[PDB]
Amino acid sequence: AQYEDGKQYTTLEKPVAGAPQVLEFFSFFCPHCYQFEEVLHISDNVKKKLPEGVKMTKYHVNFMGGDLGKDLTQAWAVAMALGVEDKVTVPLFEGVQKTQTIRSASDIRDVFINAGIKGEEYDAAWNSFVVKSLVAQQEKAAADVQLRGVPAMFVNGKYQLNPQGMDTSNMDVFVQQYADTVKYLSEK
């Protein structure tokens, strides 16, 4: 075929019932995720081609950056609960990887404060049970899909994107192929 198992995607030996339709995993410590987010805009470009009635879910993962890694997963939960993903994603990536000014939970908080979220509102979200289960959700989803590496994308708990199996000398073309694959798997 043109899209073959093992080529642009793999198939899960152990499918995951009831999974989010399009599910993406990343980490602010993950250099390819950095590339994926502000150089390639993968998340974006996928949406632009998904049929609609399709929702997209992005979760953070724990297994990079130890203690900070976990702090970041809670912070991403706060971001989701507050609906401020698009105001913190870039400063968080650049704070961890570019300037390296994120070294503690408090520094993560500064990014939110600077992005305009209020202290009391941040601290309350942080400490809230809704954010605890939203952490639990992120972990569960990662747990369900054998996850050892990021970036990672899964479609309908059955298919996993395989970006290594796509051309990379043109970035624009890599993205389009990636998004079209997601759209194919979607209709499967």
Image (spheres, rainbow, N blue to C red):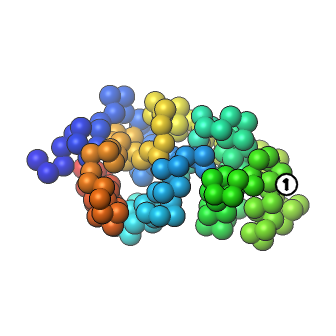
Q: Determine whether 166 is above or below 68 in the image.
A: below
Residue 21 x %, y %: 41, 50
Left or right of 61 in this view: 177:
left
In front: 158, or 177?
A: 177
In this view, the residue farthest toward the left is: 1
* Residue at horizontal 69 percent and vertical 58 percent from the top: 99
* Residue at horizontal 41 percent and vertical 35 percent from the top: 16
* Residue at horizontal 65 percent and vertical 38 percent from the top: 65
In this view, the residue farthest toward the right is: 120
In front: 169, or 53?
A: 169
Residue 175 x %, y %: 34, 61
Instruction: Please tell me whether mark 1 sits on a helix, a strand or a loop.
Output: helix
| Image quadrant in which you'd find residue 186 | bottom left
Residue 36 x %, y %: 46, 57
Q: Determine whether 68 is above or below 172 in the image.
A: above
Left or right of 20 in this view: 168:
left
| Image quadrant in which you'd find residue 47 | bottom left
Amino acid type indicated by mark 1: Asp
